Image: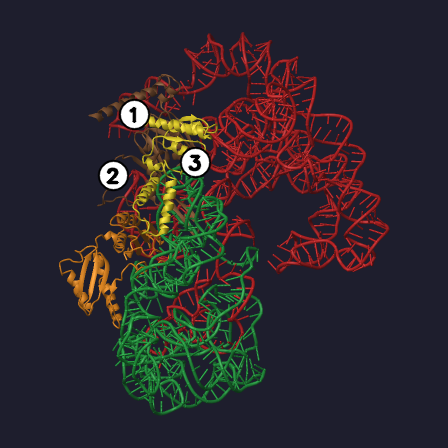
Chain colours: A brown, B orange, C yellow, D green, E red
Amino acid sequence: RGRRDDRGGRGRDGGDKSNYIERVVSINRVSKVVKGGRRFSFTALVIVGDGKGMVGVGYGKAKEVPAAIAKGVEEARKNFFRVPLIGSTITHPVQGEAAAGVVMLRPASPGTGVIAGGAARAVLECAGVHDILAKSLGSDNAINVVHATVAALKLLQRPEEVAARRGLPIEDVAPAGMLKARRESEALAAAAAREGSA
Amino acid sequence: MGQKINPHGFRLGITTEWKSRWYADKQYKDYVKEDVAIRKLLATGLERAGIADVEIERTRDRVRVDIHTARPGIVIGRRGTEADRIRADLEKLTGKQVQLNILEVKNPESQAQLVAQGVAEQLSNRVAFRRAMRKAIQSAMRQPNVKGIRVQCSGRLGGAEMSRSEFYREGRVPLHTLRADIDYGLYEAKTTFGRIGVKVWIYKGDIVGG
Amino acid sequence: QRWLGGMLTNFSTVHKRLQRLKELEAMEQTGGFEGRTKKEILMLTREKNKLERSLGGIRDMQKVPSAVWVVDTNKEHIAVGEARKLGIPVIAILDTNCDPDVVDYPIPGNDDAIRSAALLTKVIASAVAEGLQAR
RNA sequence: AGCUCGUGUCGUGAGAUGUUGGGUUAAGUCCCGCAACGAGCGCAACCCUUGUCUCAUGUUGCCAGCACGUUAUGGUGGGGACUCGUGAGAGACUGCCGGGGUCAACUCGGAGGAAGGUGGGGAUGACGUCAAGUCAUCAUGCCCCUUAUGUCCAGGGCUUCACACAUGCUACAAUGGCCGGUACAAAGGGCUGCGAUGCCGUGAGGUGGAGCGAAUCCUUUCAAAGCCGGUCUCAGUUCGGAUCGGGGUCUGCAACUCGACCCCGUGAAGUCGGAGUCGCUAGUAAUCGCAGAUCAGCAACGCUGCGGUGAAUACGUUCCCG
RNA sequence: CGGCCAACUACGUGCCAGCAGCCGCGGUAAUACGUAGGGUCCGAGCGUUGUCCGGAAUUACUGGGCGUAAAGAGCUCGUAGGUGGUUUGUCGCGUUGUUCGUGAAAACUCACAGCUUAACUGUGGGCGUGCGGGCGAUACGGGCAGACUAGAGUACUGCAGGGGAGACUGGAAUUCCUGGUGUAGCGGUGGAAUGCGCAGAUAUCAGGAGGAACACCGGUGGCGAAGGCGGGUCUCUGGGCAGUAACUGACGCUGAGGAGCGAAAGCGUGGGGAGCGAACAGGAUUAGAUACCCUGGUAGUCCACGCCGUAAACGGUGGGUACUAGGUGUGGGUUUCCUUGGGAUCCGUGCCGUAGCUAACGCAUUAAGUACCCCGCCUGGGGAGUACGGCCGCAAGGCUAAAACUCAAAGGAAUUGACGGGGGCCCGCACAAGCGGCGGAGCAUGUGGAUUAAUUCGAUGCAACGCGAAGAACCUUAC
């Protein structure tokens, strides 16, 4: 990924809507032996997302690096994924496993900061979280820890969803501090939203 | 390795015309010598200018030197000042008198020689070579009407020690078909690390037009 | 005739075969047969022959449909997995050996009998015509 | 005869699939299937030459029917009839019939036809390999020389020779040698070039210049092997020509080191060749001359082409090689 | 101021001199060595070395594993131990609630005050995760006292079986023996030769000896805890399964050490010794065979009595228990229905298959799935299952089991290729069928080598060597 700063007198750079947040995690040239030598190709693990908390995971195969990055962008574009939150935190401590990828995603009080390793830091920095506390146990990789983090975010659910599963009136599903954090986060959603209307 | 014959020399009987045209018995070696020194004399300032084709028709010892380029305005500066200087030096180097016709190609991105010009002159200018190859292409495919597009760049690419050849294309470029109308142009970039020889194949169409 | 793999998920490639089929039939109403070499004419006879005999419905489709009706979820598994993958609801016939969890709106029954299967085709085809009448 | 790619699907991933299966092909040629559907570079086709005919076609080319030659022949008035020369066009497509084919591709036979199934041969080298070759064709990055590693000339060398390899040529003879008579080519080459009749030589050649920038003139009307005849009688020879001596001619300022050719003599090895190994499947192999480029001359037995005469064998994939 | 890891250019040496935490940088164009500019990070400091915690979920209580990656004892029985179905009562030992006492000060944490600020110091809380006393609770664990029948075991009726041991015996075949019949070969091999023969072999017939192994049934089949077990019959004995529910009433599970069983080879003493056969000869093959192949051949293989204790003792999967879609074979037994056919059931053993699981292959009601109980075991590769020491053993050896040192890996599964003296299907003057040659002779050209003042320079498997040269007397021409 070099020589991107450019000014063209051509038709268009085609800049348009959906200015999302896009992170390229790792690139390892992938070789293939054929008759008389090696054929080098490229893999780019592409994370895309918006600051609401919708995450994509794309996996680009091409024999050029920006081609593989662009194919990962289109593949994560094809496949988004909804993550439920509280304010800008996570709901409750989970462990995700993608066959060797263990990631523990635990919430924290706000202000602490996204503390995670670089793959999980990528998937969570694209997402709508600002203050959680994760760790990547096992598998020491990028692909399995990204995919394990997304499986960990599939083990998430709303407080309300849990209440619904059990047919119980909330209050009765959460404890009270987390309901107060719901009041804080929806209150600042009201403040920034009504400042957004004017 | 790739033992690929120059396709403008592989279809020079069938589709592509000769560049130089006369008849000569016992005057032929002299006409060859004048043809060579004329093309060396039209190498430098016209390769600054954007030269593509240098045809020399030759009637009863006058001469007619015709050049197809991509900017009438650098070849013809002030009228007669830039034209009649190289024209007059062609009149003095040859022992003859020169009728220099200068004409523009309707699309510079259509000619394979001029694509090799713009690519190699970008590649001497420290740009990214894969970015350069992509730039020349795509835009060329649409420009006028091309079917083939082969850009091979060998040499010290990016200043590296290994001489890596690259091979990008789009569409149909059949070399073994003789009704191909393929334009071919190889021009050689001059970096400080060395020379990056650029080959460009451009397949315009199936049309014989016999 | 034969379920081509990747009709629904890959529509952007198999639509090009359709426009080439339109250019073939529009050059069949043209009448250029003798001006070309007959190896190319017999070759286009093979292209129109196979491409018309195997592709008849997407000739009318154009439009990445909202529903799919499936006979024999077992044998036509490719269509049911592709139809599930886009989010398109599946309406099917289900024998004793078909997994009903892949089909959202089933109609259970034997598929081996032409009377029963063909009658259920009459059911849902009359249903679609009943949709067309009030529209 | 393969090498890939796009988009879809499969897989955590490298990747796969497509491109595998059934049949078919000179061929990933082509059909039928199949989570693939398509494309691209190859293969084929387009181009040149060879094989048949049609139309056009008349000099420098042909000469039948005409006329005139006599010595020498199309040599000459003439003629488009035959060639031939070069332009356009037809013609081979499994197109037509029989059988196998899954009623698909394709294969076995037959007819017509100059030609039958990619008719013959070319030109045409995919993605890449081998750090293959070339900084001496050229161009060139960097390093080195700049009082020499530049440059000018004479002489020498690149041709030396106890050897060893490699590709060729002439042979070892009677399907042959030598003398005499005689018949048939194709293509080419030519300006300070190709150079005829005639004369002088034994012969390289000398003297001379006809005539041609060449379907015309010259390379003789072109060949050699072929055919008819005579002689040689199986031998180190009328085989074989190396070597060496004498005597010349031509080219060039100059043939000593180092040119070719001719004449006279000289007359060696060599009796079909160990282990092995190479080429070739039809106008091929084998053998026979001819021309060309480079070139003042030639180390040309080389290279590139042209034609002449012209075979044997292929049961078949076990074995060696790719 | 390569990468991690904020920060790059030139000059100088070109596998040297040096660098480096690991990966790794130096073979005349190093952003990795040395010097320079320049940048970055810190700052009265900044680097190095050592020692500890961290990252290391890498000794995993919180928080790991054991089919193939390190890792399931060869298999059982059982001592301590750990663990415990249903239910009534009681105790208050575990557990829990509360209050009292205590946990010195300092530190630590929160607030505040004081020193120009801060470090620092002080005041007041909290912390002091604990322990002892009093009072309360009784679900769960436990103790005691009882009750129950589903687990466990017993009785009864059957049933299947190479389960084991002892004893007696059967035939086919191999070898030798005596006797016929009868002649020059037999045997053996890719091809042969040592070898047995011509003194009567091999061949065939009759009889005799003796030993071992059990054709056919017999296989993806039965039984055993695992090793393992197949001629027959008899005698003694072990386990399993089903059915009824008659009895006992939790007597269960596992099991550190421990005892027992445990293929083959091997060991001791005494028998036996046909076939096969290590070692050991000769023969052959081969460069050479201390090998394969051949001919002979001793211990051994066999039995009696003991040792030994090991195996790819492998399902590479410790034992127990409950649950979790199915489909189809076959083994043992009960019953409802058609009336042997299906159904249902309990126990067994295979093949395919969801969910789920796994690194992947795979597993998948006979789990590698979901959970509980107990045991074994693993902690990078070598060094090494080795030394030292002890224990057992007649010995061979087994068991238990390190360190220095060294490496930056050693591994598992799958992928793309190449490769195979792997398989299949194909082709090419690839072989076969022919014809003509080369290799021996003379010369012509080119190369090697040696010469030389100079023998200019290039091109050395196929794809260099009548090749750059389509013309070396001078020129060419580089020497």
User: In front here: D211 or A12?
Assistant: D211
Chain assignment, label 2: A
Q: Amino acid at mark 1?
A: Ala
Q: Is residue E204 above or below residue A162?
A: below
Q: CA distance from mark 2 to mark 3?
A: 38 Å
Is disc 3 placed on a helix, strand or loop? Answer: loop
User: Residue D196 falls in which quadrant of the image?
Assistant: bottom left
**In the rendered image, which residue does mark 2 sit on?**
A15
Task: Indicate left or right for C46 with B116 as reference.
Answer: right
D316 lies above or below D244? above
Q: Are marks 2 and 1 on the same chain?
A: no
Image coordinates of residue E347 in percent, x first then y, are: 61, 25
Q: Chain ID for label 1?
A: C
If the image is split into quadrants, where does the N terminus of chain A sit? top left
Marks 2 and 1: which is nearer the front? 1
Disc 2 + disc 3, Cβ < 8 Å: no
Say if A57 sits above or below D148 in the image.
Answer: above
Quarter of the image for the C terminus of chain A: give it.
top left
In terms of secondary structure, where does tag 2 sit?
A: loop
In-front residue for pair B156/E381: B156
Q: Is residue A13 visible?
A: yes
Q: Which residue is mark 3?
A: A139
Q: Read off the chain for label 3.
A: A
